[PDB]
Length: 210
Image (cartoon, rainbow, N blue to C red; front, side, top):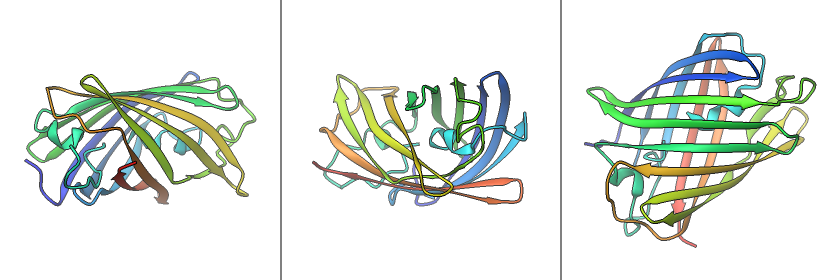
C-alpha cells in the first residue's frame, strides 16, 4: 500500500548522441503532498558531457497532490503500478525519448527508465553544460479511453537567465482499469542541486481543476 513516506530505488540506462550512461539512486517523498527528494549518481559513462537537466524529468506521478474529489489515475494504479513514454522536442532541433516503469518491491517504489537523446548541437547550451533549472511548469492532462496524455511546454533556464524551449508529450498507462479523471492540469516545480558527485532533485506537483 501507500504511506506518507515512500522510498524509491532508481535505475536508468541511456544514451545521448552515442554516449552511453547509467544512473542509480534513491528517493523519499510524501505522495499525498506531491513532494519528493532524490539522490542520484552516474554509475556508468561519467562524467556526462551534457547538462543533467535534460534527464531530470525522467526521474513518478504517484507523487502528486490530488484534490480529494478528483480521480487519481496514478495512485489508483497501485499496487501494480504504471508506465509512461515521453517525447521531448527542443527548439534547436534536438530530440529525446524516454520511458519508465513504476512498480513496487518490499522497500517501496522501483523506478526503471531508459533515455535516448539525439542531435543536441555541440556548441549549444546542453552540450556546453549551461543548464541550471527547469522553469515551473503547467502540464495539461487529458484522458483518452483508459490512458492519460500529458502536454507541457518546458523552459530550461541557462546560466545568465536565458531559456531554452522544449515541448514534452507523455502517455501514461496504468496496468488495469481505473476510474478516469477529467481533463485537468498538474503544476510542477523541479529543482536541481548537487552534493559532490551526487545529483539532488526535488519535485513538488499539484493537480488542479480547470
